[PDB]
Amino acid sequence: LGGYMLGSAMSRPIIHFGSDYEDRYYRENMHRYPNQVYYRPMDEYSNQNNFVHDCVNITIKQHTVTTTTKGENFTETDVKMMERVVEQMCITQYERESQAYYQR
Image (tube, rainbow, N blue to C red):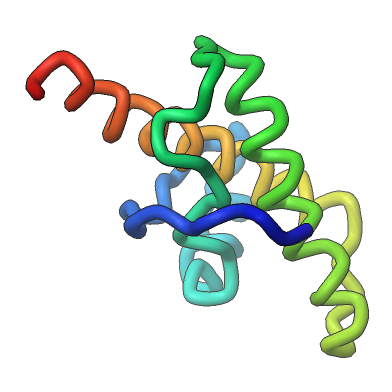
């Protein structure tokens, strides 16, 4: 996992899991969860959600791998929480640079 750059940061979004505890558990700890995503400048092929799929996957996985070796045992919930958040971040990132392709 090289040959990629990291965009600006965006405000760690509070996707609701349907239970205030999951919301707050994340929230107080939201400093731990990622606030940026791996992307490219406009890429070469642009997509609604398939971009998000891989943009998320790589960013999610880059937590999941490292965290294991930084002595932080992350379970399905420490990933699935993050997943919704990284999905947002990749949506936001796509929409944030692709918007300005129509303003050049």
